Amino acid sequence: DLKIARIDVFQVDLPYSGGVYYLSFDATIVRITTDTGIEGWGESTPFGSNYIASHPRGVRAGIATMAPSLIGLDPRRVDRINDAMDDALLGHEDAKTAIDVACWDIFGKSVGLPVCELLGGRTNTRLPLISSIYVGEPEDMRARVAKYRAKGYKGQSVKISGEPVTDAKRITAALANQQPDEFFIVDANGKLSVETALRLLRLLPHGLDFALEAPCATWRECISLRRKTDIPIIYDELATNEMSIVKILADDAAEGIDLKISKAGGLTRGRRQRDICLAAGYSVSVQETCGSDIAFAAIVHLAQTIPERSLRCILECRDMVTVKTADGAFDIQDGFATAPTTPGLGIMPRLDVLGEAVASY
Amino acid sequence: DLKIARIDVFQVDLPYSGGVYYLSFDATIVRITTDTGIEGWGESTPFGSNYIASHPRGVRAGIATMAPSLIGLDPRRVDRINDAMDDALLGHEDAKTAIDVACWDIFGKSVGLPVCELLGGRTNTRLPLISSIYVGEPEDMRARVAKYRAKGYKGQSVKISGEPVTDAKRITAALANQQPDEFFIVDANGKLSVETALRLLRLLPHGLDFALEAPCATWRECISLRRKTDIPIIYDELATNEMSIVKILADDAAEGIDLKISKAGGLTRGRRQRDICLAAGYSVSVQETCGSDIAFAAIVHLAQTIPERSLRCILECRDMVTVKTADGAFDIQDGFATAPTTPGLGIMPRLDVLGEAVASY
Ligand SMILES: [Mg+2]
Ligand SMILES: [Mg+2]
């Protein structure tokens, strides 16, 4: 009754809004067209190739291997589509993401409903945006946190380098005037060894309220650290597909996850993981490795289905870039947003920015 | 004093010697040339894209992302080369493999020594080849096991489907006349759920001597099963880089591993893992996902450095294909082989078979 007739891949250079990130992004955007003419869009944009086992060339290569096997399938059967992608290629959540998201776009358009409504129904609360406080001198970090607070942000992500003594001063300053209505995350991006994590935690003065995200690079190290601290731990890099989330629960390894759409594998896997976390009482932040307006659409729709008490902000990933790839109303107002109310993802890509497809199936 | 001047990538179709595998291979071969003219070779050939998170297009895409960063580095500093590959791209052991192996080839040629001698020194014992018994009717499997026994093979790998009742009959028949000098492996290739693994193990009659390889798809399932059985367990698909091997030890999860060169990340990582296993008392089989004569060279040199008591056969991966990519003397004789004694890997590629490079850096 409805079949995938074509899968087109586009490539877009997305300049970094921060100029240069020390220690532009190559975005992969996919358009799926059904036999009836409905078009759906999805995106997968890795944060370089050093964040997790993912890179731009890898995303497109993965799509090339899977795409042929998807032609003729019903895009509305999102779980079956994912089963099919899994049968064609193991892992590669980053390559599967854009395809899955596009199917959801088509799905919503086919029944005339916003994606969040097909994901269980939209909540009646707004979505808090989270700030990104890059590593710098303690006072600089504190000032930037203040700038965001003055813009209405209620969530802040403080990055650290991995050098415990200075990091301690950075966290102390960054949280200097934290308020009762703010949620703070200290993100180590897997840069701490257990030794360094313990040294950092022991150096911190009392009174600092935050959750520690991605403390160490490997599962073993994070578990080892978990046994020696009472600080809330959030998995990000190590939280990949739904099988990894179940492992977190089996190991009582953390208190929540940073659910990045393209690391999870799309909205379908995002839903699977959402339900695992909500069933367990884990907190969930919805973000992305990186991405334009299209990737942001997926973030907002998934987040709009997570009860406020369980949500830990969302990342307006498009803030990381300077090129607009699509139009959409996300109702942004002083640090908060809400999912659109039109069919599908609620976005309309700018074909001129996408250029001609780099691949077609 | 010695630097990488060029990295060329070749692609070779390798027809399956078994005709068609149910439920040809695309081989990636790399040639590294130093500024002084020394050439080294390496290979990475995935067993399709369903075995592990690896595919042909992915191997080459990974090389494209890493290669530029390697130009100018000393190929002899194998561990530093691997550190550099890690700095350019996380994971992707499959893409790193061919480059690492080629550096070892260069390394051995530069000092006029076989790779196994630079890996710690060759043992004085022969390397037993292992058979591959594809799934079939019980009697057919038993007959094929007999065929290999009659050829002098002392190692046998019996594959199963994942259907416990029939699998039990298959294992019973396949091992019907196993001898005192033979080592048997039953490989589930991660196809058993804990439920199915338990049902299979409970159905088997007493007296069957074998080690169970890759029983379940995920780490959690394998640990769960480990707690409910006393059968030796060997990790294959889940044994990836050295960090995973340390995790096996931390979890007391298995008795040994199936070390596949391209899954491990090359000879350097192979050495790292070898030492972890030998230090622990874990058994080690040296194989490959798939591969021609070049990939086979890496297998033999690593295996020739593992004490006989700890080795669990090697896979003559080239037996899986019908196209010869290089000449080399592996001293094959009735189910046994030994590493060559000439410099480097001891192989000379057939340039005519490789065709023109598909990529150059
Ligand atoms: Mg993070
Ligand atoms: Mg195996």
Image (cartoon, coloured by chain):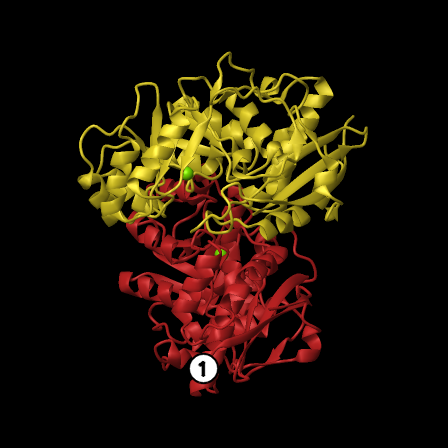
Chain colours: A red, B yellow
- Could you tell me which residue is drawn at 61 percent across and 65 percent down? A28
Residue A26 higher or lower than A122, as above or below: above
Specify the quarter for ligand 2: top left
Position in image of residue B120 (x %, y %): 56, 18
Residue B260 higher or lower than B276, as above or below: below
Position in image of residue B169 (x %, y %): 24, 40
Q: Amino acid at mark 1?
A: Gly
Residue B242 higher or lower than A346, as above or below: above
- Could you tell me which residue is drawn at 34 percent across and 49 percent down? A253
On-image quarter of the N terminus of chain A: bottom left
Position in image of residue B203 (x %, y %): 18, 41
- The reply to whether residue A130 is in sight is no
Mark 1 CB in 8 Å range of ligand 1? no
Position in image of residue A361 (x %, y %): 60, 69
- The reply to whether residue A250 is in sight is yes
Q: Quadrant of residue A180?
A: bottom left
Viewer-side residue, B334 vs A257: B334
What residue sits right under mark 1 in the picture? A108
Count of picture labels: 1
10 Å crowding of disc 1: few (<14), some (14-19), many (20+): many
Residue B334 higher or lower than B221, as above or below: above
Identity of the residue furthest to the top in this view:
B124
Q: Quadrant of residue B197?
A: top left
Viewer-side residue, B170 vs A61: B170
Determine whether the residue tagged by mark 1 lies in a helix, strand or loop.
Answer: helix
Q: Chain of mark 1?
A: A
